[PDB]
Length: 175
Length: 173
Image (cartoon, rainbow over all chains, first blue to last red; front, side):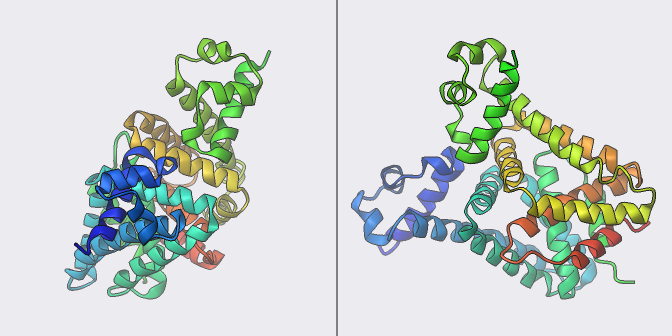
């Protein structure tokens, strides 16, 4: 099964989501991935590469979520509506994804090297956004999506879609 | 005896440099230089302690919002002040960046803490509402959040121009 390496990455993500970044260790991960301890160092040069590849995988996943919503939009109007859907789904559908997102941000805040990950994440998000909006608005919009998602997710009383749709309409206005 | 204050201070310090998982009564008591019993006496537990520690941090940030939007006498002066706020909030203190992120992770994991992240947003909108209508204040607070995070976790933060244009659009009408 050539999927042992992939399983290690997934178990690493599960571990971080459930117990936090500080609990990351070769032994704990091997157990969750159901692979011998030696498999950790056979496939990975160290914890950094492991973490980079793990968060990179999580990163690919969310980017695909952008693709799922935006790729199905025919014009600006559907795109704006699609973005609202994206914001609400990201803010409440998966607590695991919200936690992994926040873990990554804390890591990148602490260790600059990991900002290569967040930088590449923001860039890919913008790519799909630029399939409907110009580069500038796409950048402004990505920051809005980030903020709306965060404020809904950590809210005691999350705002509704009308408010989300209006902010989106406003940020994507060029008249 | 400012033991309570020192404990709250040591808590933020520990979280800021060592990470949330390193918080324990023992370690914090050590940092603050107080007897282990002080931790259990002044606080009902780690929850109430983190709640008050982070509560102090948000006071610190809300204070920054003020003294920024504080002296704008215009909607346009307000906009430029928000821009300044965004850039200062993303470059000046890595401590504050880390602490905001630690709070965000805790609230994501334990909904109970979403009470203070909720109160933070509320207190932020209060200052913003001094210049903009309620709906706009709310949308703006979210944009401020997103722009700040994107500038901070980028390899090359975007320029002031981008920040101001985004603000100009979200505060349109």
